[PDB]
Image (cartoon, rainbow, N blue to C red):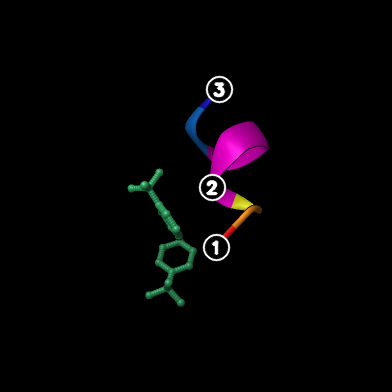
């Protein structure tokens, strides 16, 4: 999940 969201940054 972390990667899925982190892509924003
Ligand atoms: C630790 C998080 C998931 C916030 C992150 C990892 C790698 C690049 C950007 C964010
Ligand atoms: C340090 C960066 C943000 C390049 C990173 C750490 C862990 C996973 C993916 C990227």
Determine which residue is flagged by label 1. 9
Q: CA distance from mark 2 to mark 3?
A: 9 Å
Q: CA distance from mark 3 to mark 1?
A: 14 Å
Determine which residue is flagged by label 3. 1
The answer to whether residue 8 is left or right of residue 9 is right
Counting from the top left corner in percent of width and height, residue 4 is at 66, 34
The vertical placement of 2 against 6, above or below, is: above
Assess mark 1: CB under 8 A from ligand 1? yes
Q: Quadrant of residue 3?
A: top right
First along the sequence among labels 2 and 3: 3
Q: Residues within 10 Å of mark 1 (few under 14, many from 20)?
A: few
Region rendered in magenta: 3-6
The mark found on residue 6 in the picture is 2
Q: Residues within 10 Å of mark 2 (few under 14, many from 20)?
A: few
Counting from the top left corner in percent of width and height, residue 8 is at 63, 53
Q: Are marks 2 and 1 in contact (CB under 8 Å)?
A: yes
Q: Nearer the viewer, residue 3 or 5?
A: 5
Point 65% across, 53% down: residue: 7
* Tag nearer the camera, 2 or 3: 2
Counting from the top left corner in percent of width and height, residue 5 is at 59, 36
């Amino acid at each position: 999940l972390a990667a899925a969201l982190a892509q924003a940054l």
